[PDB]
Amino acid sequence: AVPKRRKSRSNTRSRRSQWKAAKTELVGVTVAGHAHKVPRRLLKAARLGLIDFD
Amino acid sequence: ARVKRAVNAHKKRRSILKASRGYRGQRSRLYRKAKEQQLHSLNYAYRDRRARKGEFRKLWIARINAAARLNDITYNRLIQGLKAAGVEVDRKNLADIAISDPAAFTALVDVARAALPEDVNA
Amino acid sequence: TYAIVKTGGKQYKVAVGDVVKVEKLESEQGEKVSLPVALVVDGATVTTDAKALAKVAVTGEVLGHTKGPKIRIHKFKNKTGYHKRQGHRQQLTVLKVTGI
Amino acid sequence: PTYAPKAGDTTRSWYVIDATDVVLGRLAVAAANLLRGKHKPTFAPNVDGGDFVIVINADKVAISGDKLQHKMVYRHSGYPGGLHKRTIGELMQRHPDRVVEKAILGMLPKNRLSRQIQRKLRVYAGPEHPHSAQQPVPYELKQVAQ
Amino acid sequence: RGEVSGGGRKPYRQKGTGRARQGSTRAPQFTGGGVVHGPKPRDYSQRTPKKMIAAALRGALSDRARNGRIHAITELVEGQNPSTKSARAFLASLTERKQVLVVIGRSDEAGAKSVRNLPGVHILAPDQLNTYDVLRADDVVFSVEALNAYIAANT
Amino acid sequence: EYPSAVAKARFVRVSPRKARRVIDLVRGRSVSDALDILRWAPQAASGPVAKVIASAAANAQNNGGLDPATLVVATVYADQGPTAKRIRPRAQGRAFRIRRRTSHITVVVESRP
RNA sequence: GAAAAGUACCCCGGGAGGGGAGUGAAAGAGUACCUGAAACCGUGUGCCUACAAUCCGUCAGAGCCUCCUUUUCCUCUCCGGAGGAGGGUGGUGAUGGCGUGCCUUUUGAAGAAUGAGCCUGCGAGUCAGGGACAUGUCGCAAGGUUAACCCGUGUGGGGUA
RNA sequence: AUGCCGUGGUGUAAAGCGUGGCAGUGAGACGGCGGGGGAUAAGCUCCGUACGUCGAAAGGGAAACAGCCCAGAUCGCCGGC
RNA sequence: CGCGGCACAUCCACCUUGUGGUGGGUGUGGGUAGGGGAGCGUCCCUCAUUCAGCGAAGCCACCGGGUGACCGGUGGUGGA
Ligand SMILES: [Mg+2]
Ligand SMILES: [Mg+2]
Ligand SMILES: [Mg+2]
Ligand SMILES: [Mg+2]
Ligand SMILES: [Mg+2]
Ligand SMILES: [Mg+2]
Ligand SMILES: [Mg+2]
Ligand SMILES: [Mg+2]
Ligand SMILES: [Mg+2]
Ligand SMILES: [Mg+2]
Ligand SMILES: [Mg+2]
Ligand SMILES: [Mg+2]
Ligand SMILES: [Mg+2]
Ligand SMILES: [Mg+2]
Ligand SMILES: [Mg+2]
Ligand SMILES: [Mg+2]
Ligand SMILES: [Mg+2]
Ligand SMILES: [Mg+2]
Ligand SMILES: [Mg+2]
Ligand SMILES: [Mg+2]
Ligand SMILES: [Mg+2]
Ligand SMILES: [Mg+2]
Ligand SMILES: [Mg+2]
Ligand SMILES: [Mg+2]
Ligand SMILES: [Mg+2]
Ligand SMILES: [Mg+2]
Ligand SMILES: [Mg+2]
Ligand SMILES: [Mg+2]
Ligand SMILES: [Mg+2]
Ligand SMILES: [Mg+2]
Ligand SMILES: [Mg+2]
Ligand SMILES: [Mg+2]
Ligand SMILES: [Mg+2]
Ligand SMILES: [Mg+2]
Ligand SMILES: [Mg+2]
Ligand SMILES: [Mg+2]
Ligand SMILES: [Mg+2]
Ligand SMILES: [Mg+2]
Ligand SMILES: [Mg+2]
Ligand SMILES: [Mg+2]
Ligand SMILES: [Mg+2]
Ligand SMILES: [Mg+2]
Ligand SMILES: [Mg+2]
Ligand SMILES: [Mg+2]
Ligand SMILES: [Mg+2]
Ligand SMILES: [Mg+2]
Ligand SMILES: [Mg+2]
């Protein structure tokens, strides 16, 4: 099966705009006084110092 | 002498693309497709310039019929009576009158009704 | 008051002070023209009669000569190689109604 | 140029038609014309002029007995063998208002504007309607003599 | 396409490929291919009869004479040493127009060299007069010997 | 309208579509929020984009002398850069082309209360 | 670039790259470099679009947005015009009618016959000959004309076979 | 009955005839009328028809609908029959 | 049919009374293969003239024009 004809700009764009990244929600944490923002699932690691904030 | 085509050849391309502004798809972007759409567009415009006279007459007739039946007479007999009375007011102006001066339209209806024959079926 | 003036093969509903674009008249700019009418409404009266109307004319003043919109024609037929381009620009005359 | 209706130009009124003995086709034509606004000199085919129409006593409309016995109403569900037929008699037994509404809708122009036009139609089977807040003036079918 | 380098063999198979058959790589539709009906060396020259040639030259000189643009001089420079300055002064005295034709004998080297490099001055021998040069010239300047030679040649 | 600073990253070796996927996450946000959104974004193109945004903020603070705490990512987009072409051999002697696309990433940050 | 005068120095950055400075008439010439079109890909923005069956246009046509002018109003008016009305540009197009893509080949194709993904550039009645026929025009005219060749800086003058 | 030849009148611009230059065409289709072949079937096949349309003809009508009915588009008009 | 613009042919009178123009009647102006007539645009040479580092070409936008191919003006970019 091969495409019968090339898609139109609108038809291509409607599908192409659905390929996007989901944004992760971030919470606030303070380590050694400095305050950072981390994803909530890493809150325990951030508190215990296993997170390298760079 | 050898002549490059580009300078001469771009004039019709620019004109066609300028004329095809507002089309959607390839029809406003590519010269070859805009050319075909231009052919169709100008044929449609030529046909519709002639057909719109009939369309406007149709609209006028409909509005005149509405006003006549409001004044209790058919379009049939209103036109026949106006012809008999020798009133040569246009259909366009008749519709304009019907919308703008209903009293004048009523007066015209009485004139046509008077000019109508005593029995229209003889 | 207003009237239905006949000119150039067409009819126009005009009142005093109106400006109308009509077909070209062989009249220069500035001078006056008198035109026949098909109906005169002066409130409740319509006068609806050839004899009474033939003695009434509207007086207009030629405001100038203009042109209609440019019309482009490109006649075309399906599989023939037939094409025909053509342009047109109708000549018009502008009237200012001052009479009735 | 000829008059072109603007937004806010159009005015609407309320009409109530009693269908106690009117022929179905006659009633449908009258209602369709009223809905579309063909009775007004300001009519334009691209503008939804026209007035609200209420039909009462829809169960009393005049239909011939052979029509009640033989006129079919068809529907296809989309599945194979999905054709369902009922007689006008059964339809009048169950939903008399639907017979009238279907007749009226068959007479409107088949375009988008008719979808918005038909929203002004109310058909009731009994002699009562809830729109007493509006004041529907009675409308009777008349024929202008020619 | 027969003279472009290469292009001898058929590039690939006619059938079973899905592409246009091509015959040679130097076909005119190819980039770098041959030129169709292109320029070749040509000889531009016509067989105008002598009677017409002579009549045209005579008409040109007649126009010049009738309008009064014909001058005759004995010589251009007094001595045997060319002097562009004096020659230019002499022609400026004779006429003031941009283009000048000078007809002098083939043996008058001092006169030739004196006006050789003056802008707007053209030199030719009496037996080499022709319509293009005469019509280009605003004025015609004859040496006496040149004028007599031309008149004697044409009887 | 607002004081601003610009930064550009030309010839970055990431496909423009892949760069857009992460740019759309931070367009319009403040610099501080955009930086950590890109920090915790799992996509690989989050690195270069974060570098450009940080460089633009640095330009604003250093050259323009603007307060870093008020910087907002106002404009950001990714254009196509030059594309290099490679060949991938396939079955039965066929040879397919491969494109190595690059991007030009432009960021404008402006300071506003 | 006329000339390397090919960006000292500082900043972000592992680099790449960039910003500020600086050179230059010009960086709207930064060794990816004269000019810098189209296809193609973004970002901002005005209008429209999630009850509708659309060869994608055309004719009719409301409503919005924008920019200018004629009125009456803020008369602060030297203002300027907010704003009110009218009129006109330009953008968009709810809604109504009409409407079977181009080429080729065919008796006949919107055709479910052929060909074309798109743009830019290139790609097909030419040249030779005192050839042949017919015409327009010019010179000479019961005559017209030279070929080879000769002489001239040439396109000019000779040359009767 | 028509059709055909000649002749005298009347009418009719873009008929006709001669001689040259330049062609294209030589696969036609459907409909009406008269016939052959076929089974008096074929959207079948072959002839005739100063018969028509299409081909190479747009517009209105026949729901749509080369060949049927009306009618031959120089252009413009928001005029009329 | 009405009113206005265009073109071809013919006729009628004027101007050089056919090389052709002036005005007025009448007819005509669907069109494939094909025949005839007249034009637009690009480049090069020659003659005359004219513009150009106070900005040529090319490109882009806008505002206009012609019966057609097409044209002009203004601005921006650009650098012969
Ligand atoms: Mg499978
Ligand atoms: Mg649009
Ligand atoms: Mg008509
Ligand atoms: Mg055909
Ligand atoms: Mg070879
Ligand atoms: Mg071969
Ligand atoms: Mg090569
Ligand atoms: Mg070559
Ligand atoms: Mg010779
Ligand atoms: Mg192998
Ligand atoms: Mg400098
Ligand atoms: Mg420059
Ligand atoms: Mg430059
Ligand atoms: Mg490049
Ligand atoms: Mg460049
Ligand atoms: Mg909706
Ligand atoms: Mg449908
Ligand atoms: Mg539409
Ligand atoms: Mg339809
Ligand atoms: Mg076939
Ligand atoms: Mg096809
Ligand atoms: Mg298909
Ligand atoms: Mg087929
Ligand atoms: Mg085939
Ligand atoms: Mg096939
Ligand atoms: Mg294909
Ligand atoms: Mg030649
Ligand atoms: Mg001859
Ligand atoms: Mg016989
Ligand atoms: Mg012949
Ligand atoms: Mg044969
Ligand atoms: Mg045959
Ligand atoms: Mg038969
Ligand atoms: Mg038979
Ligand atoms: Mg057959
Ligand atoms: Mg037959
Ligand atoms: Mg054919
Ligand atoms: Mg037809
Ligand atoms: Mg015919
Ligand atoms: Mg038809
Ligand atoms: Mg009638
Ligand atoms: Mg005709
Ligand atoms: Mg013709
Ligand atoms: Mg032809
Ligand atoms: Mg300069
Ligand atoms: Mg040039
Ligand atoms: Mg320029």
Image (cartoon, coloured by chain):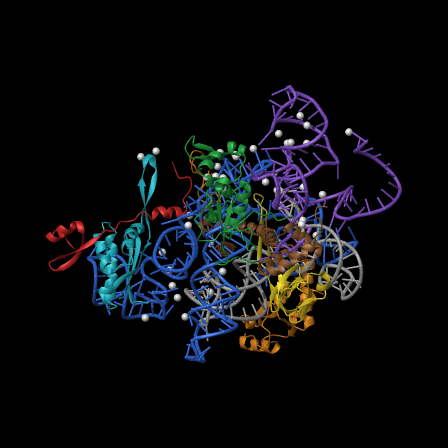
Chain colours: A red, B brown, C yellow, D green, E orange, F cyan, G blue, H purple
Look at 54% across and 35% down and name the residue there.
D64
Locate residue A38 relative to residue H77 in the image: left or right: left
Name the residue nearer the viewer: D22 or F51.
D22
- In the figure, G30 relative to D97: above or below? below
Left or right: residue E6 compared with residue A17: right
Above/below status of C74 relative to E142: above
Q: Tell which of B59 and G7 is nearer to you.
A: B59
Please tell me which residue lies in front, F69 or B19: F69
- Determine the image quadrant of residue C14: bottom right
Compared with F102, H56 (above or below) is above
Between B31 and G139, which is closer to the camera in this rendering?
B31
* Count of marks placed on residues: 0
**Image x and y of residue E78, in percent:** 58, 77
Q: Is residue C74 visible?
A: no
- Residue C65, given in percent of the width and then of the height, sits at 62, 66
x and y, in percent, of residue G60 in the image = 54, 55
**Is D119 displayed left or right of B92 in the figure?**
left
| Residue D45 shows in the view | yes
Percent position (x, y) of residue E68?
Answer: 67, 73
Residue G139, quarter of picture:
bottom right
The quarter of the rendered structure image containing the C terminus of chain E is bottom right
- Left or right, D74 with respect to C9, comes to left
